[PDB]
Length: 134
Ligand SMILES: O=C(O)[C@@H]1CC[C@H](Oc2ccccc2)C[C@@H]1COc1cccc(Cl)c1
Image 1 (cartoon, helix red, strand yellow):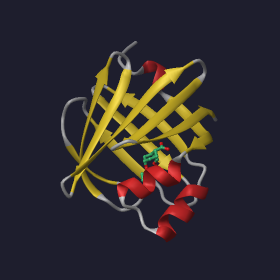
Image 2: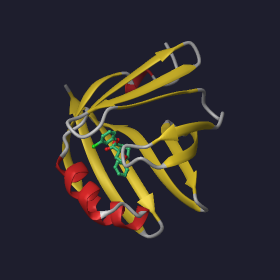
Image 3: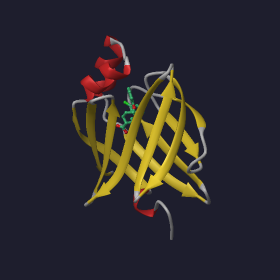
């Protein structure tokens, strides 16, 4: 057993708060905000050795990232940003920092009861996205 055991599995989005304002802060345009904001993604998290994989599947876009903790990688986000990402574990929370165009956003993922809670922060704006097991 290991580092991210409690994150592994298949998860479905059940609630979202303040996501449009977060996307606006990130710089997402109108049409993408509308379509992306409708989506109810499934997130599939797996671990193989040191490599963590997070897949998301939705009506809007499918994305996939594989990474080693602390080791920067290139990511294409669902809104088509080309970012440089670093993901670490801080006290049981996955902390994902994305850098692009001189900007930065942080996504934190934690287990809370039977949920996986995703908090997305850009400057002073937070969005909270809650997932349940699928
Ligand atoms: O897990 C979440 O809900 C985070 C939400 C913010 C980030 O994504 C963003 C998505 C759109 C705009 C800005 C940022 C990462 C993940 C969600 O990734 C996906 C992947 C494919 C399709 C969809 Cl619709 C969302």
